[PDB]
């Protein structure tokens, strides 16, 4: 089968500990992925379903 | 030094509709709002059979008729769901403070989820009750071919 | 989810599972030698060819 090629990503997806995650890391020693996402789902749109 | 919550994921359940499976190709679905009053259903057939006239002396059967009756069969489906008494109560109360609000939509989500589970598991019942009706009336192939 | 069963039998209640996966940590090491003489030469600026 004359394909021999696949489209892929050329760079890794990055994870960084920012100010929100960083504060938790210092104070409680626990870090959660996408604090942005958790806050968007808890504090901002609670009514909205998944 | 920390420990990281990498992800949280919830299984998502797709709805299953009887009128959208190809099993319904063998069925004719009519809705009946108040079927719960019907005592008995019935279908009556009348069929008249022709003959061939013959030169031979042998007696010929006269005009024939056939009348066949069929009857309805009822089916029943039941499901059970359980809910906490703490959960139904906070549905009524208005949320006073932000923690009492988050705990609140956590209750409406749960009650709603239970309801989805109840109505969904009713669609699986239609698909099964129909499929079981067939396999109850499907004679085996090795008997059927000769008889056709 | 479950199926509503026409057969007479006790129904099953709504259920959920909670399953936890956790990481594995991997460690990788390599060794590099830098000549003492080479480092000294690099530090200075060269004059003669």
Image (cartoon, coloured by chain):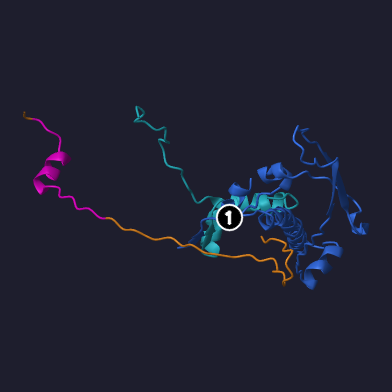
Front in this rendered view, residue C21 or B41:
B41
Say which colour chain B has: blue
Residue B56 location, quadrant: top right
> Chain drawn cyan, letter?
A
The span picked out in magenta is: C29-47
Percent across and percent down for residue B11 are 60, 55
Q: Quadrant of residue B60?
A: top right
- Outermost residue to the left: C49
The quadrant of the picture occupied by the C terminus of chain B is top right
Q: Secondary structure at mark 1?
A: loop
Name the foreground residue: B65 vs B27. B65
Tell me if residue A10 comes above or below residue A41 in the rendering: above
In the picture, measured across the screen, residue B71 lies left or right of residue B80, that is right
Q: Chain of mark 1?
A: B
Q: Residue furthest right?
A: B37
| Pointer 1 residue | B9
Is residue B68 in view from this perspective? yes
Indicate whether A21 appears above or below B51. Answer: below
Q: Give coordinates of residue B105: x percent, y percent.
A: 76, 58
Residue most extreme to the front: B57
**Magenta stretch contains residue B49:** no
In magenta segment, residue C46: yes
Q: Is residue A12 above or below residue B136?
A: above
Q: In the image, residue B136 lies at what x, y percent?
A: 68, 58
Q: Residues within 10 Å of mark 1 (few under 14, many from 20)?
A: few
Which chain is rendered orange in the image? C
**Residue plotted at (17% across, 41% down):** C43
In the rendered image, which quarter is residue B72 located in?
A: bottom right
Location of the N terminus of chain B (image quadrant) = bottom left
Answer yes or no: is residue B93 visible: no
């Amino acid at each position: 089968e004359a394909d021999n090629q696949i489209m892929g990503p050329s760079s890794y997806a990055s994870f960084v500990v920012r100010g929100e995650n960083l504060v938790t890391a210092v104070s409680y020693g626990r870090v959660m992925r996408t604090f942005e996402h958790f806050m968007a789902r808890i504090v901002d749109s609670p009514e909205k379903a998944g | 030094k920390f420990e990281v919550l990498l992800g949280v994921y919830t299984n998502a359940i797709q709805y299953v509709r009887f009128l959208e499976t190809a099993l319904a190709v063998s069925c004719v679905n009519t809705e009946f709002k108040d079927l719960s009053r019907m005592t008995d259903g019935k279908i009556q057939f009348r069929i008249s059979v022709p003959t061939i006239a013959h030169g031979d002396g042998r007696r010929p059967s006269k005009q024939r008729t056939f009348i066949v009756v069929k009857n309805c069969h009822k089916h029943h489906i039941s499901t059970e769901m359980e809910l906490s008494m703490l959960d139904l109560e906070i549905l009524h109360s208005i949320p006073e403070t932000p923690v009492e609000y988050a705990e609140y939509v956590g209750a409406v989500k749960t009650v709603a989820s239970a309801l989805q589970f109840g109505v969904d598991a009713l669609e699986r019942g239609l698909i099964n009750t129909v499929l079981s009706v067939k396999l109850r009336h499907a004679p085996p192939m090795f008997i059927l071919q000769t008889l056709a």
